[PDB]
Length: 313
Length: 302
Ligand SMILES: Nc1nc(N)c2ncn([C@@H]3O[C@H](COP(=O)(O)OP(=O)(O)OP(=O)(O)O)[C@@H](O)[C@H]3O)c2n1
Ligand SMILES: Nc1nc(N)c2ncn([C@@H]3O[C@H](COP(=O)(O)OP(=O)(O)O)[C@@H](O)[C@H]3O)c2n1
Image (cartoon, rainbow over all chains, first blue to last red; front, side, top):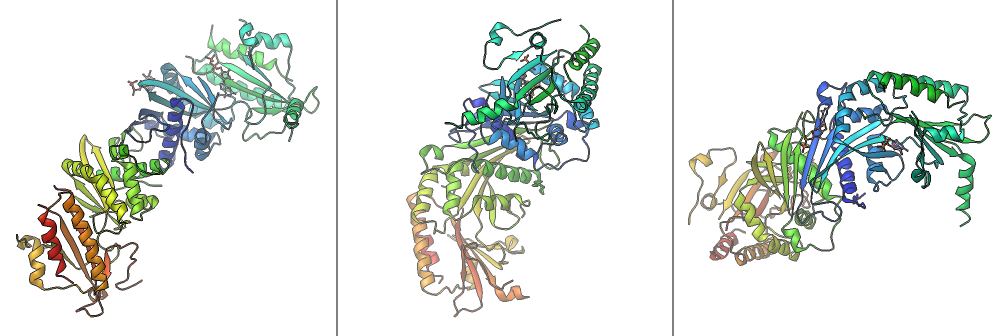
């Protein structure tokens, strides 16, 4: 039952301690009927000065700040995520890979800037309104928590989201789609490259999701990018991951010498199975990412939507 | 859901803090032994909330625990489970500075800076004594020492186990330590703390028998010899009497000796049927001869 908070770097130990602490505190606060405006301006701040005490894995001195915890608790709920699940994914064992996921591949933690935190604040009220109006059905990032860590006097901002990719299905290819950009030879020659727009058009990959799936997808994406434009946001990308059912079927047995393509929409919410009549058996993960940035954002909406339309069947 | 609702805000912080520290402690393993740094150690946390969780807590406060490994171990050596300790302090606000937990199981006393200094001066020898007598002792059982800062003003507290039964109403009180007696002022309260002389005037005796009295005396002698060997004085013996029959105006004169650890039933050959609670108190204010006179006083009462 004993959480040690052991991690490779002290900041991660503090991250685990902080999420554990704040979720436990959150469990003694009742759940409100609605959020009040003050809930959107609030924060929790704790400052720890231990001494000759509990130093095995944590620092003796550190600080942890959580932003709008009532709000992200509500978001967590509206996205179908249990607080106990959230805390466990972050604390049963250290996250891994600044860019991290929890041990269980369920959630992503990104280090971010002061400015990103500011923008998140400027948009949070309208974003929560959007999430609730669409019952959480959106390809936008699902923000579950925003925290600030101070260790060795250095502040570090982090934003927690749900992973776009399946937490079980191996992802075989990745694209970042938003002028004309392509993957550097440097990126092109690494373990799993983020292949930009130009490489996707060069390769001629299309995604065969089947009529009904494609339509629900495009309706959802149109609602979302129009929201982003109405918030005067741009430079956002659509993230795309390909899982090859048959290759996975092989490797889970090739390591064995030493359902297939089945997934849970309650967990892998951006996942989509390939059309029954498709060249190969694939699973796709597609969602919008990178929306805290702030040439025209209206034209951004229109161009982005036309491109993403022309990448599906 | 622990709301930490309390009578005065300092009590809310006490509840939050003991809750916090006991939960943190449950993620700290139990060491093979205590090390010297454990006797110099401390936990310190500082809270600045804002537009958040202000219903029952303050937005800004600070909480310090002294020697958490030691007091946790003491707790164990006194037969006290950490989760129980935490519940008694947090399931419901303490009551009536002098406090007990809602369930009347532990006493929370405000104490001075100097008292904290003294507790530190003695803690290692005291813990060693606790372990040497397997916790069977009449000395105060220190379960936790904490510093609270709320509105920038610090408040020190020591938690100990209660002398009296947490269920049985106690009917008369004597504080035995020269010549001290109860003032007309003190004499005119609901339960007076009647000092040494008035108990001898009243002519109440306590009939515990022989075997009971004998083992009791062995324990009292051990304790005061320890306190002398540490050059401590001005300590008092607290004694409370429960007269079952007055209570009659589920169980009568019934208690759990694992819980009311200082209780004793009266001898069959006794004036009335009584239950007695006896333990040493106020041992933080720093001749030896006090040991001998004190123990002699307590000798002639069985
Ligand atoms: N639109 C908006 N609304 C808010 N409600 C809000 N809140 C914070 N930001 C921004 O990010 C930083 C947050 O940490 P803060 O710097 O504020 O944290 P704090 O000031 O306590 O500590 P420091 O002074 O030791 O850094 C701020 O400086 C801002 O750049 C906010 N932006
Ligand atoms: N699997 C998965 N699930 C998520 N929820 C998720 N969210 C963000 N990524 C990552 O965002 C990174 C770029 O991040 P981006 O915002 O473009 O910032 P830059 O790196 O350009 O500064 C991409 O390479 C993705 O790996 C995610 N990956």
